Length: 446
Ligand SMILES: [Mg+2]
Image (spheres, rainbow, N blue to C red):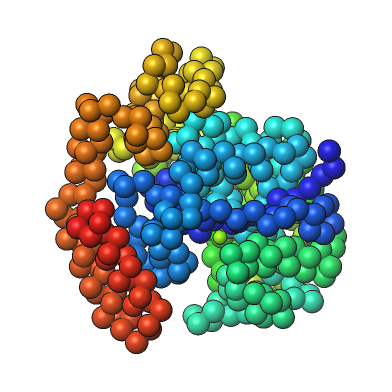
C-alpha cells in the first residue's frame, strides 16, 4: 500500500454522538499530497423506528428522516461500508472536528453493530488527524498568509464555512469533505513547516517525546477548551500521568490561578487550572518557544505570569500527588460505550455475531459475559433485522418504543415543531422541513 488520506464527514440527526443517529456519511480518498484518487463515497443510514431526529439538526442538514430511510441502508450495512473504508492499510482518517464529534459517531456506530470501536484508527499503520486544531494552531502560532474571520461576537471563528469564505475557497453532499481538503492544502502551502510538524506529531510517541514530567517542562498547547478569546492557546506544564487512563497526562495551565492547587485539598479540588491532554487524540503540543513573543502579545498571554507559576509549581512537587488524587476516582445500553473494554473472549463472541448471517442469529449458540452484550444484540437485531424477530421479541421491541416515546417526550416534540414553524415562518425551506418532521413523527410516534 501507499499512504493515503481518507477525508470524511457525517451529517447526523442530532448533537449527541451516541444517542442521536447518523443520517449521511461522505468520504473521499487522496494520495499523500491531497490529490483525489478515489471516487466520492456518499451514503445514507436508515433510522430505526425507536427514534425521532432533533428538529434543529434537520434544519441544518436539510436531510429528513424520510429521505435517510428511503435512500439509506440499515445501520449494520452503513457500519460495514464505513469500516471497509477506514480499515484500508496506511490510511490517515481525518475530517474537520472529527476528534470531538465524527470519531465519536464512528465509535458508537461500531459499538452498536459489533465492530471494534477502536482498532480501525491504528491497525495496519493507520492514523487519524483533524484539521480543526490545525487551523486553530495556525491562527495562534503562525497566522501569516491566512485570512482569519471574526464571528458576530468579535472572536476568531473556526467554522469551516467561515474559513473557506474568508479565504476564497468555493464551498453538494461532498461540500464539506472537499472544503476540508481545500483547508489542508491551504495550510500545507502557506505554513509548510508547521503543517509538517503537526502531521508528524499526530503520532502519540512523538507527542510523548515532548513530555518531561520530572522537569515540568513547559509546552505550548492549542485546545478549544482554552477559548477563542486567547486564540485557544496557553503554556502548560505536565505534573503527572493519569492514574487510570494510560493515554492521559495531567497538565497545569500556567496562565491560570494556581492558588486552589496550592492551598486546597484533593477532595475539594475534585477555578482549577488543570486539564487532561489525551495523547491518542491528536492534541496540539509544541516546545514553549513555538509561541513567539509577538503572538503571545497578540493573544494576551502573560509570559511572566506563566513563568512565576511554573517556578512555584517546581518548588512544590507535592502538587503532583495532589492532582493524581483528583483523577484517582444511564440504563440505556446505547450510552454505555465507555463503561469498559470488553474482554478478549467477549470480543471473540461479538466477532461471531458480526460474521453470522442475520437469518442465522436466532439460532446462534454463543456465550457473552459483559452485561451490555445481550441488550446490544437485541437492539441490533430489532433495529436492523426486524423480520427475524419472534412474537416475544416483537413485544419486547414494542415496550422499548413505548419507553422511549414517553408522554413528556411526545408533547415536547410537538411543542418544539409548532414553536419552530412560527419562529421560521418566513423561511419557506425550513417550514417545509418542519412539516416533513411532523409527518414522520405522526407515523412513528404521534
Ligand atoms: Mg462535520
